[PDB]
Length: 49
Length: 48
Image (cartoon, rainbow over all chains, first blue to last red; front, side, top):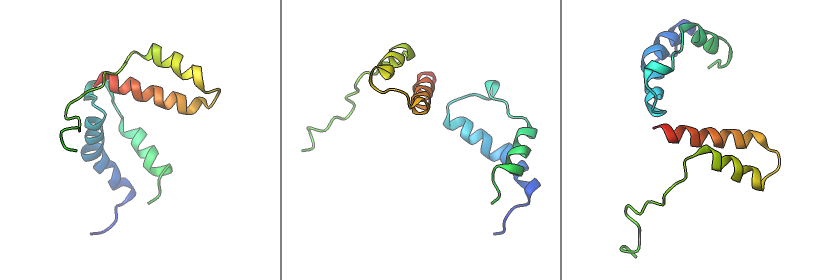
């Protein structure tokens, strides 16, 4: 298995990651939107791994 | 040793934030960050 391109992490997190954690905190999608833009900002800046 | 163990004994919690507000300000000056985080913790458990 390889690493992941910077853009690629967006398509991961948009599907398989946010909903999972959304289920860990007990929320429903109706109340906790996260646009794509906040995610691209995150991965671009706050975590380089 | 086995029978003594609670299996479902459920200490009742308080869950109103108000009483948590008070009791946290009663016993620790300052260190407001940890107070705010723990307060959020109770706030989330009260929902789900």
